[PDB]
Amino acid sequence: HWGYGKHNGPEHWHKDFPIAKGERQSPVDIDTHTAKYDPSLKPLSVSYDQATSLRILNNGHSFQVTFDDSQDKAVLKGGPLDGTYRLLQFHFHWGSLDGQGSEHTVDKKKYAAELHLVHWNTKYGDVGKAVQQPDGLAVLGIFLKVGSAKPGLQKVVDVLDSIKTEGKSADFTNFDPRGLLPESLDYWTYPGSLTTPPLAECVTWIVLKEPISVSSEQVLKFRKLNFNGEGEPEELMVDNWRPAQPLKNRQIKASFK
Ligand SMILES: CC(C)(C)C(=O)Nc1nnc(S(N)(=O)=O)s1
Ligand SMILES: [Zn+2]
């Protein structure tokens, strides 16, 4: 089964998921000088006030916080998007050290981690149908750098002890994802894919220019999670990032000058 190790990592994924070598794979390097300001791009609309978080889960890849997506509660609109995209889950990718961990890069710079808020287009009715569409998902990507703590992340960090190994989950209600957002909603956008199998080419990527800062203690708690299930040889869940993929016939657009 796929993972991030030497024998099952990103360089192997194409064997089970041939779209890994596709025309719109993610992540990519964002070359800030080549991204073109698009004045026709709207401001992003992030409407998270009514978000209902449900559970936090170690899925063997990452940890994720899942939301109730059975109603338009926490939605992403505007920007490059047509229609309404419901927040389903967020998760992170991170490194073994602070100089790596992000999936997208900015002028080849890697951040310590990257937060993905995954939303699906309500015109397709459910996320499984949305994954089969070129505009089915919108993932809001936010870079994490190490410095000051992000207070809004601490509730997440403090429960990771209870989901150390693959398969473990916990109640995680009343979590407000607005506490994870940076000040600016300036973004880059391009058409891409899921960055984990099945690597489906269904994502409008919206990557915020402004990172959030998290503390060393916060990211260290990410690095104590395990890829393995309980009772299996302990393999720290670190470096769960796919590297940048070829941009191919794509333009990255910027919402800002
Ligand atoms: C809900 C569902 C389809 C299982 C999902 O979200 N899958 C993702 N696979 N890769 C993602 S990423 N790292 O691009 O945000 S999300
Ligand atoms: Zn992700």
Image: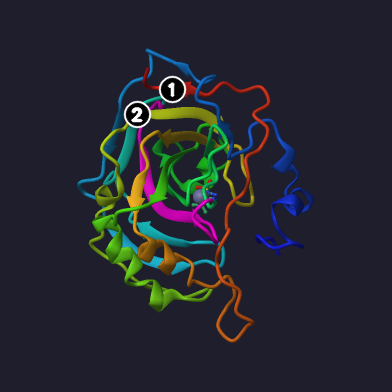
Side of 206 where 191 appears, left or right: right
**Relative height, residue 25 to residue 159 (above, below):** above
How far from the left and from the top, in percent, is residue 187? 39, 30
**Residue at the farthest top position:** 39
Identified at 41% across, 62% down, the residue is 219
Answer whether residue 134 is visible to the viewer in this image. Answer: no
**Residue 199 lies in the magenta stretch:** no
Element marked by disc 2 = loop
Side of 91 where 241 appears, left or right: right
**Residue 85 lies in the magenta stretch:** yes
Q: Which amino acid is tagged 1? A: Ala
Identified at 34% across, 72% down, the residue is 159
**Relative height, residue 36 to residue 20 (above, below):** above
Does ligand 1 reach within 8 Å of label 1's beta carbon?
A: no
Identified at 37% across, 12% down, the residue is 39
Dot 1 or dot 2: first in sequence order is 2
**Relative height, residue 49 to residue 201 (above, below):** below
The span shown in magenta is 81-99
**Numbered badge on residue 206:** none
Q: Which residue position is annotated with label 2?
A: 186
Measure the C-alpha gap from mark 1 to mark 2: 8 Å
Q: Which of 63 and 95 is in front in this view?
A: 95
Q: Which amino acid is tagged 2? A: Asp
Q: Bin the neighbour count of mark 2 within 10 Å (Cα to Cα): few under 14, some 14-19, many 20 and up.
A: some
How far from the left and from the top, in percent, is residue 45? 28, 32
Q: Which residue position is annotated with label 1?
A: 254
Identified at 33% across, 37% down, the residue is 76
**Residue at the farthest left position:** 49
Element marked by disc 1 = strand
